[PDB]
Image: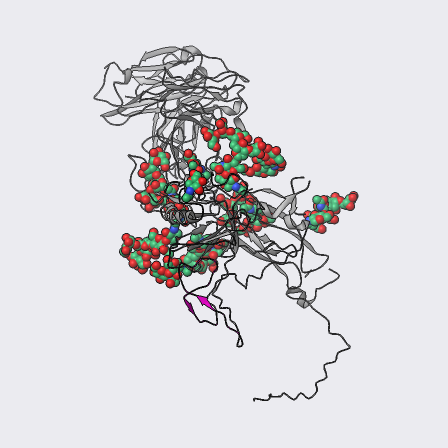
Amino acid sequence: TLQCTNVTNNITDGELKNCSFNMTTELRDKKQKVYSLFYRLDVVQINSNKEYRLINCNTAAITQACPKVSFEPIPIHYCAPAGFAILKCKDKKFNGTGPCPSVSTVQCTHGIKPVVSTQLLLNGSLAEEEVMIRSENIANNAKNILVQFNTPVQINCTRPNNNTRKSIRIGPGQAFYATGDIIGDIRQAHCNVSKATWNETLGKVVKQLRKHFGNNTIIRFANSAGGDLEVTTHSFNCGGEFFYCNTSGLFNSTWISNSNDSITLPCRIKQIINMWQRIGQAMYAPPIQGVIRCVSNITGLILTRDGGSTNSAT
Amino acid sequence: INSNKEYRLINCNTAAITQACPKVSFEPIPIHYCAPAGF
Amino acid sequence: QVQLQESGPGLVKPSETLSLTCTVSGGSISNYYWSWIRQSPGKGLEWIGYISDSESTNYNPSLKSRVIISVDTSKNQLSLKLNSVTAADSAIYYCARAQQGKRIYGMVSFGEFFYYYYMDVWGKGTTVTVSSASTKGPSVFPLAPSSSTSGGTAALGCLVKDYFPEPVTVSWNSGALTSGVHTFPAVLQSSGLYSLSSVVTVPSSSLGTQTYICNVNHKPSNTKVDKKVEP
Amino acid sequence: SYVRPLSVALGETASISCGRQALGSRAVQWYQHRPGQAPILLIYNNQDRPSGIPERFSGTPDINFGTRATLTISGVEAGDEADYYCHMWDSRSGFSWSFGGATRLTVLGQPKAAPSVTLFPPSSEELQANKATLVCLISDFYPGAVTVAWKADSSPVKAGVETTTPSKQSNNKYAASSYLSLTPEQWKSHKSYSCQVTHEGSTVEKTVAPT
Ligand SMILES: *[C@@H]1O[C@H](CO)[C@@H](O[C@@H]2O[C@H](CO)[C@@H](O[C@@H]3O[C@H](CO[C@H]4O[C@H](CO[C@H]5O[C@H](CO)[C@@H](O)[C@H](O)[C@@H]5O[C@H]5O[C@H](CO)[C@@H](O)[C@H](O)[C@@H]5O)[C@@H](O)[C@H](O[C@H]5O[C@H](CO)[C@@H](O)[C@H](O)[C@@H]5O)[C@@H]4O)[C@@H](O)[C@H](O[C@H]4O[C@H](CO)[C@@H](O)[C@H](O)[C@@H]4O[C@H]4O[C@H](CO)[C@@H](O)[C@H](O)[C@@H]4O[C@H]4O[C@H](CO)[C@@H](O)[C@H](O)[C@@H]4O)[C@@H]3O)[C@H](O)[C@H]2NC(C)=O)[C@H](O)[C@H]1NC(C)=O
Ligand SMILES: *[C@@H]1O[C@H](CO)[C@@H](O[C@@H]2O[C@H](CO)[C@@H](O[C@@H]3O[C@H](CO[C@H]4O[C@H](CO[C@H]5O[C@H](CO)[C@@H](O)[C@H](O)[C@@H]5O)[C@@H](O)[C@H](O)[C@@H]4O)[C@@H](O)[C@H](O[C@H]4O[C@H](CO)[C@@H](O)[C@H](O)[C@@H]4O[C@H]4O[C@H](CO)[C@@H](O)[C@H](O)[C@@H]4O[C@H]4O[C@H](CO)[C@@H](O)[C@H](O)[C@@H]4O)[C@@H]3O)[C@H](O)[C@H]2NC(C)=O)[C@H](O)[C@H]1NC(C)=O
Ligand SMILES: *[C@@H]1O[C@H](CO)[C@@H](O[C@@H]2O[C@H](CO)[C@@H](O[C@@H]3O[C@H](CO[C@H]4O[C@H](CO)[C@@H](O)[C@H](O)[C@@H]4O)[C@@H](O)[C@H](O[C@H]4O[C@H](CO)[C@@H](O)[C@H](O)[C@@H]4O[C@H]4O[C@H](CO)[C@@H](O)[C@H](O)[C@@H]4O[C@H]4O[C@H](CO)[C@@H](O)[C@H](O)[C@@H]4O)[C@@H]3O)[C@H](O)[C@H]2NC(C)=O)[C@H](O)[C@H]1NC(C)=O
Ligand SMILES: *[C@@H]1O[C@H](CO)[C@@H](O[C@@H]2O[C@H](CO)[C@@H](O[C@@H]3O[C@H](CO[C@H]4O[C@H](CO)[C@@H](O)[C@H](O[C@H]5O[C@H](CO)[C@@H](O)[C@H](O)[C@@H]5O[C@H]5O[C@H](CO)[C@@H](O)[C@H](O)[C@@H]5O)[C@@H]4O)[C@@H](O)[C@H](O[C@H]4O[C@H](CO)[C@@H](O)[C@H](O)[C@@H]4O)[C@@H]3O)[C@H](O)[C@H]2NC(C)=O)[C@H](O)[C@H]1NC(C)=O
Ligand SMILES: *[C@@H]1O[C@H](CO)[C@@H](O[C@@H]2O[C@H](CO)[C@@H](O[C@@H]3O[C@H](CO[C@H]4O[C@H](CO)[C@@H](O)[C@H](O[C@H]5O[C@H](CO)[C@@H](O)[C@H](O)[C@@H]5O)[C@@H]4O)[C@@H](O)[C@H](O[C@H]4O[C@H](CO)[C@@H](O)[C@H](O)[C@@H]4O)[C@@H]3O)[C@H](O)[C@H]2NC(C)=O)[C@H](O)[C@H]1NC(C)=O
Ligand SMILES: *[C@@H]1O[C@H](CO)[C@@H](O[C@@H]2O[C@H](CO)[C@@H](O[C@@H]3O[C@H](CO[C@H]4O[C@H](CO)[C@@H](O)[C@H](O[C@H]5O[C@H](CO)[C@@H](O)[C@H](O)[C@@H]5O[C@H]5O[C@H](CO)[C@@H](O)[C@H](O)[C@@H]5O)[C@@H]4O)[C@@H](O)[C@H](O)[C@@H]3O)[C@H](O)[C@H]2NC(C)=O)[C@H](O)[C@H]1NC(C)=O
Ligand SMILES: *[C@@H]1O[C@H](CO)[C@@H](O[C@@H]2O[C@H](CO)[C@@H](O[C@@H]3O[C@H](CO)[C@@H](O)[C@H](O)[C@@H]3O)[C@H](O)[C@H]2NC(C)=O)[C@H](O)[C@H]1NC(C)=O
Ligand SMILES: *[C@@H]1O[C@H](CO)[C@@H](O[C@@H]2O[C@H](CO)[C@@H](O)[C@H](O)[C@H]2NC(C)=O)[C@H](O)[C@H]1NC(C)=O
Ligand SMILES: *[C@@H]1O[C@H](CO)[C@@H](O[C@@H]2O[C@H](CO)[C@@H](O)[C@H](O)[C@H]2NC(C)=O)[C@H](O)[C@H]1NC(C)=O
Ligand SMILES: *[C@@H]1O[C@H](CO)[C@@H](O)[C@H](O)[C@H]1NC(C)=O
């Protein structure tokens, strides 16, 4: 239990915190107080000046990822063995299921990069076509939707704080990576999209779904309205710390009867995550020091209807 | 580090330790490495 | 093209209310913003607060107990009153003219800025200290020339000895002359009163009697005094 | 709190340090101060500067973090003599209500100006007021480091011994006065009286006598 309150700033925008705190040194009976900088979501209060406790402490353990390993995704080619074979389909207007007339033989997948993303996909494959996309059964709401593009538009997620860090030794060989002093401005995590391309790739996502709810019908959009903190917003990895932006500006339009203007999308950054909806030992994500900047290539998205209401009205 | 006097274990600085089980012994014995059929 | 002057009646008793106004003859004052600053000898400058045309006020941390400042539109100028002055608040004060710029570390919405407040053109300043003293006028005596160095040049000055604060006009012939001027600021005495001297350098061929008249004023005592000097 | 000192040589340009060093992106105002009269202004953004000011001084612009506000004072002269104030406004510090600490400068490398004394006895109607007193005047002397002594011929005074400390005109050199509480009795009792200064390691200092 490791006391803190707000971080130095003119009171503007749970931005972040700065606790000062007990710890065990390499020697046993020896202890030490030092400070670090956490974020709103990693800790929750109980009682004094004041002081909270780490959100996961409630239910699970944590093993911090070794910063020697990195989570930049790389192409993976899954392979069927001798005595078997994979196979690929090769018509562009193919929808989710059905026999494929154009077929050619592969044994190992093309390069799939395992991007950890919730509600959107990007830097993925892109069909030479107009983005025709499928469900398990569109007629029902409960089973998701999975778009993916024809020409990708760019995405660059940002927070321009140069974090500092400091290795400090917990004990025999264990070195905890405390986040250190911020030097420079205070700056929130966000992400840019020029609507010019967004609304027009949108525009072609608009017209094709029509071929399943009539060519004369309403369509709609606003923000996610159900679930937990992690999936209601864009969970993903960029360079070592994970993002969570409300996609508010994006889901902003109704299109019926058929200067830069760049969207900017606020995100919050996490460090300790119970991923893949699995309770158990958490992972503490070490910080990232200096600037950050990640370009990106939107290819797809994931959606789910809400269900019961008047048929085909709205 | 500092009294009457007292020190700390040289490795405490950088690493952990697991003591060898005295049931196992490190007397060396002949080992014959082997190539398999097909080699 | 915008100008200044500040008006202090003098010194008001301890535990009391200040009154100072500083009029401007430059333009429209409901378009901008004029604050206050304080010099005090043996200490540094200090700034204390402000307020707007759209009446948004502000004070200085150590001093916000009872500073209140509201300004007039008919008379384009500011009117500051305090309450409960100590001997320490003794000081010359300049009405300070603040021009604002933005800065921003980025793009407005995000949040994105403190605003700086920098200050263009201010006033000569009007002097006010504070102590429990009344008002009296100076003493006025002439100290004739020497008959100094070889002709031409010679010397002559006026004496003013016993007067309440040092800040007093002392013009010569209503400012007809300013050559060779040097008025010495005064010396404080154990009695507790400034004592000044002020002198112009003359030539011995200039002599003599061409109506040099020494003209001194002093407002808290409301004294108007001139004095004819002669060898 | 108070003044902290920096000295430079005449003709040549030097540094200026500042306290209070910023934490985030900067926007520091200056203020040139002269004791008694209005503090002028040399910049408003670390980049640009008001009108009518010589195009010499200039703070360091916020190009990246790593910069620390600094000025360089070319063509030094006695006119640059003043105290100035480094008023800070950074990204995350709150409303900055104090200025920068007062900062000294004196220009070094302007050799000295000898004083010049005047000396003009009590009034023709101070005598009647039952009081009498005459005061030395001196002019144009650098440095403003001078002691004066008053002189009953063959005996100093050590009475009514209060004088200004050297304060300075618009000629850039200092001035001073020394007043002499006396009585009209011992004023005529004595043949003459003096009041002679000790600027530098030199003298030049004459006397006066009653009518
Ligand atoms: C994602 O999408 C986002 C959405 O579009 C996008 O957001 C952008 O983010 C970036 C950063 O991520 C932002 O960049 C910053 O922008 C700041 C502001 O720049 C704008 O505003 C100023 C101010 O305008 C006033 O002042 C000028 C100057 O006199 C007047 O001429 C104007 O008329 C105006 O005055 C009126 O308006 C005021 C209100 O603003 C009123 O108060 C006033 O009374 C008047 O009514 C403009 O000058 C800027 O124009 C210039 O820049 C743009 C590009 O930004 C050019 O297109 C344009 O042609 C001009 O060149 C612009 O309009 C910047 O101040 C800031 O840069 C300073 O700070 C950084 C860090 O703090 C420093 O490293 C940097 O050096 C800069 O400091 C300079 O300036 C300061 C202050 O002046 C000086 O003190 C300092 O010495 C230094 O001077 C140097 O540069 C000077 C010129 O800058 C020069 O004069 C000097 O000689 C010296 O060389 C920073 O760049 C950007 O604002 C966001 N966009 C928007 C629209 O807000 C984002 O990029 C996207 N991508 C992501 C997130 O990855
Ligand atoms: C998160 O929470 C944490 C809580 O645990 C926060 O951590 C705390 O943060 C505060 C920040 O306010 C720290 O306070 C600072 O402590 C300084 C320690 O003092 C050292 O120096 C003393 C004497 O100097 C020796 O060492 C210097 C090198 O440092 C050396 O050059 C010199 O020759 C000499 O050997 C020494 O006795 C001490 O033991 C330390 O070693 C202290 O100096 C700081 O004082 C500042 O700030 C105060 C604020 O009012 C000023 O009034 C002071 O004048 C002083 O000003 C500084 O800046 C001036 C310019 O503006 C300089 O003129 C001053 O000299 C001084 O600058 C020095 O250091 C600069 C480099 O930093 C140099 O450039 C200068 O030349 C000077 O060397 C201040 O009080 C806490 O110590 C710290 N605690 C812990 C446990 O970490 C953390 O900040 C929080 N983070 C966030 C983001 O909120
Ligand atoms: C999300 O973020 C991404 C990434 O930020 C965004 O995508 C990027 O957008 C950029 C456009 O703003 C683009 O890069 C630019 O290219 C410009 C050139 O284009 C213009 O000129 C060419 C012809 O030259 C035209 O064809 C074109 O149509 C345009 O008219 C540059 O001008 C840009 O800036 C200069 O600085 C950058 C640094 O940021 C340099 O990298 C760049 O090269 C530019 O010039 C210097 O460097 C070159 C060599 O690189 C020199 O030749 C030149 O003289 C300049 O000199 C410096 O370097 C030399 C050494 O070479 C040295 O001698 C000298 O002293 C100087 O130091 C700018 O670079 C990106 O390509 C683009 N990225 C991607 C991946 O698409 C995206 O839009 C964002 N999306 C959203 C929604 O926000
Ligand atoms: C991701 O990022 C997006 C982008 O913004 C977020 O979207 C926001 O989501 C929040 C959900 O928390 C929405 O908040 C809800 O808003 C309603 C409306 O607020 C009314 O009630 C409050 C009292 O609670 C009033 O004070 C408000 O007053 C406004 O209007 C009057 C005049 O009508 C005016 O006097 C006020 O100053 C203010 O007006 C000013 O702003 C409006 C524009 O907003 C403008 O028209 C006006 O001219 C002024 O400029 C207002 O009447 C609110 O009632 C809801 O209530 C909940 O909280 C309150 C406590 O605050 C409880 O009382 C209540 O029971 C509920 O619990 C919500 O707060 C917000 O609208 C929405 N914004 C947008 C643009 O979509 C996402 O939430 C983000 N997601 C995450 C996960 O971070
Ligand atoms: C992590 O969680 C733990 C759980 O408790 C937190 O607990 C803290 O433990 C310590 C030690 O048990 C508490 O220390 C207290 O210190 C005060 C006052 O100490 C001051 O005065 C002392 C003399 O009275 C003096 O010895 C102290 O230090 C001197 O010497 C050191 C070098 O040895 C030097 O560095 C100093 O500068 C001084 O020279 C210090 O000046 C004391 O009054 C407390 O009372 C105990 O002892 C008295 C009798 O003296 C007894 O009557 C009491 O009942 C009590 O037994 C005690 O010694 C510390 O106070 C605890 N924390 C809090 C908030 O109280 C721990 O802090 C967490 N974080 C960590 C460890 O980082
Ligand atoms: C995000 O935030 C980080 C901060 O962590 C930024 O990283 C910093 O970037 C700057 C670039 O602007 C780097 O500076 C460069 O350093 C290199 C190498 O340094 C050598 O050469 C420089 C001279 O150029 C010299 O200063 C260095 O010497 C050090 O030690 C000397 C004594 O031997 C001393 O004389 C010298 O001044 C310096 O020590 C000083 O600092 C310490 C405290 O910091 C102080 O106690 C000491 O007394 C001295 O005052 C060294 O020989 C140069 O080649 C470059 O020219 C440039 O100077 C920083 O090094 C770098 N810092 C870190 C920690 O990485 C990011 O740039 C920033 N990015 C963005 C995008 O904002
Ligand atoms: C700086 O830290 C303090 C905490 O020490 C923050 O104060 C917090 O302010 C929020 C409102 O802005 C309070 O939330 C309240 O929650 C209750 C329900 O729990 C709700 O009914 C109220 O309407 C309100 O939303 C919160 O209690 C309060 N924390 C306290 C009092 O400990 C402050 O917001 C921080 N600074 C910034 C800029 O956020
Ligand atoms: C991002 O998308 C582009 C296509 O939109 C991918 O291919 C690039 O295409 C542009 C022109 O369209 C070329 O100039 C680049 O050289 C191409 N890059 C590569 C690596 O082939 C690009 O690969 C995508 N970025 C990724 C996958 O990281
Ligand atoms: C579309 O979504 C955007 C938010 O992404 C809404 O934009 C707001 O518009 C007002 C102007 O009336 C701005 O002052 C706000 O700052 C905007 N909000 C944000 C969060 O940027 C817009 O109103 C939406 N339009 C519709 C019809 O849904
Ligand atoms: C036309 O619209 C009505 C409602 O507006 C809807 O019920 C009907 O299914 C639509 N027909 C087609 C062919 O889309």
Q: x, y percentage for residue D123?
A: 37, 15
Please tell me whether residue D114 is drawn above or below residue D65 in the rendered image. above
Which quadrant does the C terminus of chain D fall into?
Answer: top left
As displayed, is residue D12 above or below residue C93? below
Q: Which is nearer the eye, A53 or D30?
A: A53
For the view shown, which residue lies furthest in the right direction? B23
Position of residue A99 relative to residue D60, above or below, is below
Q: As rendered, which of D66 and C182 lies closer to the eye?
A: D66
Q: Nearer the viewer, residue C99 or C83?
A: C99
The answer to whether residue A12 is seen in the rendering is: no
Q: Ligand 1 lies in which image quarter?
A: top left
The residue positioned 35% from the left and 11% from the top of the image is C225
The quarter of the displayed image where residue A125 is located: bottom left
Q: Looking at this view, is A95 or D60 the one in front?
A: A95
In this view of the protein, can residue A104 be seen by the observer?
Answer: yes
Position above or below: A199 against D128 = below
Query: Dominant secondary structure of the magenta stretch?
Result: loop
Q: Could you tell whether C123 is left or right of A66 in the image?
A: left
Identify the image quadrant of residue A46: top right
Position of A21 with respect to C95 (left or right) is: right
Does the magenta-highlighted stretch encompass residue D177? no
- The mark tally for this picture is 0
Relative image position of residue A256 (x, y in whole percent): 39, 40
Residue C69 lies, in percent from the top left, at 46, 21
Q: Which span is picked out in magenta?
A: A83-107
- Asked if the magenta segment contains residue A85, the reply would be yes
Q: How is this picture coloured? A: one colour
Q: Give residue A271's position: percent from left, percent from top.
A: 57, 52
